[PDB]
Image: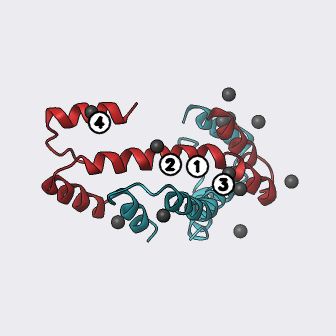
Chain colours: A cyan, B red
Amino acid sequence: KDLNLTDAQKQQIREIMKGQREERRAMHDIIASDTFDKVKAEAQIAKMEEQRKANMLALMETQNKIYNILTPEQKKQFNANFEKR
Amino acid sequence: FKDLNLTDAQKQQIREIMKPLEERRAMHDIIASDTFDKVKAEAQIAKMEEQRKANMLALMETQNKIYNILTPEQKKQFNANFEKR
Ligand SMILES: [Cl-]
Ligand SMILES: [Cl-]
Ligand SMILES: [Zn+2]
Ligand SMILES: [Zn+2]
Ligand SMILES: [Zn+2]
Ligand SMILES: [Zn+2]
Ligand SMILES: [Zn+2]
Ligand SMILES: [Zn+2]
Ligand SMILES: [Zn+2]
Ligand SMILES: [Zn+2]
Ligand SMILES: [Zn+2]
Ligand SMILES: [Zn+2]
């Protein structure tokens, strides 16, 4: 975040993120069994897609809201930074 | 997986067991837009479902096979490191 954010911008950013706001045990059970059960692993993977979906949507909506409180200069810089991360 | 004092045999066995960009650009387009298009976002998120599936399945089967070449004492170490992650 090397974009020279106005202090009104960071306030806007805090409110954005705070408004953005288990499965690992099943993964462990799959890895640590005597045999690899492919159908059971397919079902775990499919269940992980529901959480991935919710997390990607949150991430992308958050970053879209940040981008749109930016000036044309800050946007250009954000986009260059995106290309190199 | 803070390593586990693998034996020579185990190093060979792991050796044997062990035998993109378009998606980030689409995420970029969704983020750097003057509105957040949730429908297009859901489509983007789902596009690589089959590739993610084949990748996770491979990874999970690899990790299950490595787990099962471990000694009882290495299994306990691997399982305790799994719980603190
Ligand atoms: Cl766990
Ligand atoms: Cl990109
Ligand atoms: Zn089964
Ligand atoms: Zn919302
Ligand atoms: Zn072998
Ligand atoms: Zn390509
Ligand atoms: Zn890009
Ligand atoms: Zn584009
Ligand atoms: Zn649309
Ligand atoms: Zn699907
Ligand atoms: Zn399929
Ligand atoms: Zn196989």
Q: Nearer the viewer, residue A64 or A46?
A: A46
Q: Residue at x 74, y 48 (%)?
A: B30
Of all chains, the one bearing label 4 is: B
Report which residue position mark 2 lands on.
B57
Q: Which quadrant holds residue A30?
A: bottom left
Q: Which quadrant holds residue A32?
A: bottom left
- Residue B41 at least partly seen: yes
Q: Amino acid at mark 4?
A: Ile
SS category of the residue bearing label 2: helix
Q: Residue A51: percent from the left, percent from the top?
A: 58, 64
Q: Mark 2 near ligand 12 (CB under 8 Å)?
A: no
Report which residue position mark 1 lands on.
B53
Q: Which quadrant holds residue A60?
A: bottom right
Report which residue position mark 3 lands on.
A60
Cβ atoms under marks 2 and 1 closer than 8 Å? yes
**Alpha carbon distance from label 2 to label 1:** 6 Å
**Alpha carbon distance from label 3 to label 4:** 38 Å
- Residue A79 at least partly seen: no
Q: Residue at x 60, y 67 (%)?
A: A20
Tell whether A29 sits left or right of B29.
left
How packed mark 4 is, by other alpha carbons closer than 10 Å (few <14, some 14-19, many 20 or more), is some
Image disc number at residue B14: 4
Q: Nearer the viewer, mark 3 or mark 4?
A: 4
